[PDB]
Length: 350
Ligand SMILES: O=c1cc(CNc2ccccc2F)[nH]c2nc(NCc3ccccc3Cl)nn12
Ligand SMILES: [Zn+2]
Image (cartoon, rainbow, N blue to C red; front, side, top):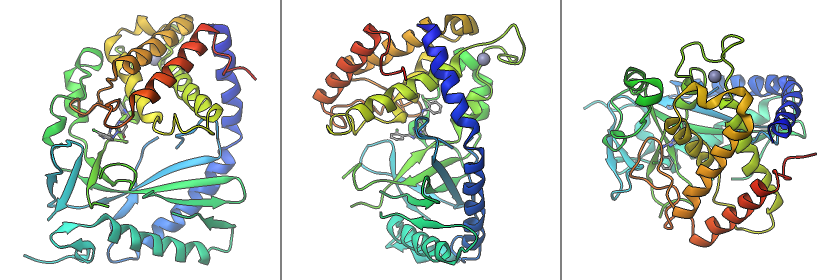
């Protein structure tokens, strides 16, 4: 119960203080690469995207970074009616035309020049040992023998969010409509997709990876939630436990393929739906950690059984569509999570 879940969280906290030094090595290499990238005519306006980092909290040495590139006067064209994937289209020509394939922006061309640069600069680094790993649209580096960094390049648009997000980000009941309006004034992002996901096609995918940070840092119905003794909630802790539960289950079954398609996306999306459904800070009281986590678990199970997990920004897109994850995989994860819940989560102890 809550006592055990608390113990897990204190365990993870100790390993977080020991990767401050590893974060320094990452920031060192990242800033070096942003500097050499800015010398390129195509990537001149590249920059770091503020997102908080760690997709894996059971592997404190694996890091995740996003570089953004602003592309002004951008025209988007939705692929099929997939809602999430888009072709990128544009009198005067500019350096980005070297990435055009016909009249659309090629992610392959752009990723290829992106990779060639980093690989060239990685070899030029002599103050630390850093290797590049084999190609999956991101670039992955190994610093020392333990630390690894995934670098994703995203296009940034400061124009209005695409129309498929119009009924999404439904946080009005929790954080108020004016916060939703504010968030929707922030830019949006487009990333290259996998050859795994989708149909090779030069479509880009909507990304809102900058939004989680905005909400997690201002997460209460109360403006002072988690800012004094009398207002301690367990939202952050429940998201951490949900993430750890999926990471642990995927490790336990890494030999089978049955869980390859589940990721922290699904847990996060399910978490923030529970925050929408339970908007009151009193539904997240620190003393009720065990009950609050159980709510998160049972909500996730319900999504699994009904095969419905709406993306948070594009509700028409079902992350748990059988078109994406087959019925048998959800049923399996349901079985494992039900077993965990029923046995006070033995996947959690030492
Ligand atoms: O960066 C993130 C993070 C989350 C995680 N959830 C989440 C984050 C912040 C606040 C609330 C949340 F529930 N979801 C997400 N969806 C998209 N793009 C849309 C999309 C991406 C991929 C496939 C289909 C679709 Cl339609 N980006 N993106
Ligand atoms: Zn709080």
